[PDB]
Length: 152
Length: 152
Image 1: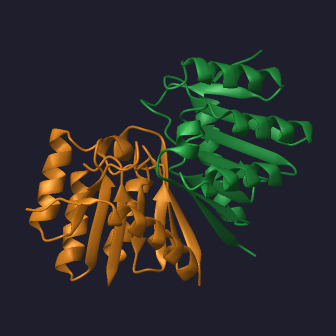
Image 2 (image 1 turned 60 degrees about the vertical axis):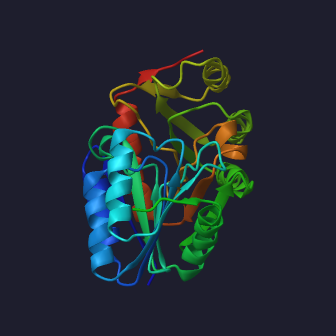
């Protein structure tokens, strides 16, 4: 039952794999991000929202004050997706997507265009490991709990 | 047979887990790093070398010109561990350790003190997935192949 997929950048497989993970969501998505700017990633998250997926995101505050960050943050908030900034860590550095409480995407891959087509990166999706995803959820929840809502 | 462990920062579990992965090596280690500066990580890599483990490292060139980077790079090179810098990517961003060609450590965790005790991070070790580790090895090898030796 448990399995693992891997993708890389700038090859193109990391981006597609991460999109695959978000597109697979049927019930929930709990995301943690440092840089938060990739438009195609944002498009995918709100389509999941539209699909009825319970989406909640906590991102690093200090590293998300740029124009692209704000455009992505506004777009996400505008779609009804609960979103929070976290500044309690010099850097909330995780690049993680927990899907349906049993799957975990993680790796070096930040959700930016640079991570999609320029930097060398890796993204893995560990499918169906309830125990692993619940542990990650506690990680996500601790950071989310100390974040500041970003609403639209 | 396959299993997955996870650790976090600044909690302390990520650092210990990554050390555990390097300490577990019996035959080989193929590492890729962006920032390369954590002293306890360097200590562990050369102890594996001493243990007779075949250790080879490719790190990002541009992000490793600082004092701590040079001290870590010299220490590693001084120990006989083949080491190369890679500048062919704006950022060789991977934080990966492939152990004994069947295990893969990856995540947001950079090999720095900041990633060990300040930033929020996650590190996972996917044990015994030969297929996954061989795929990562091709990733490591492509970057290593275009790197510049750093000798001592």
